[PDB]
Image 1 (cartoon, rainbow over the protein chains, first blue to last red):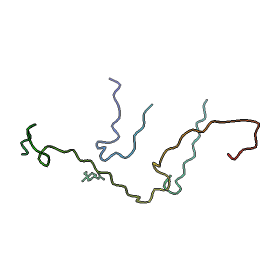
Image 2 (image 1 turned 120 degrees about the horizontal axis):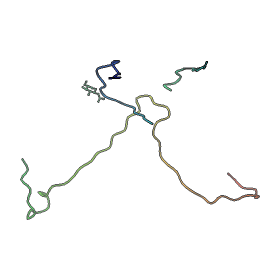
Image 3 (image 1 turned 30 degrees about the vertical axis):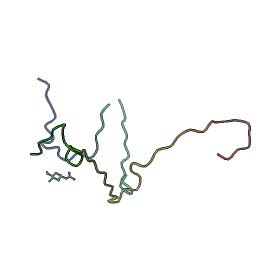
Image 4 (image 1 turned 180 degrees about the vertical axis):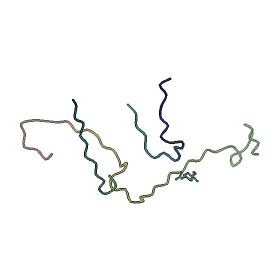
Length: 34
Length: 48
Ligand SMILES: *[C@@H]1O[C@H](CO)[C@@H](O)[C@H](O)[C@H]1NC(C)=O
């Protein structure tokens, strides 16, 4: 089985695409549309 | 329907038209123009 991705059911008008213990840190910010 | 044929005069043969249209909703750094070369040198006073 091992089936997944039940997150959404629509992906319209896409304006951007891209494809390609332990500590995993992230910093998120949103400035001038970036 | 346009019925095109090769034995037509100019003004009735099929032309292909493409149009470009820009708009800057607000983007500050989107797709811009490109650039190119200009031989690199070293050990010279230059304007770079
Ligand atoms: C976004 O999608 C809707 C349909 O869901 C469509 O009417 C609209 O034209 C689309 N917008 C763009 C900018 O393509």
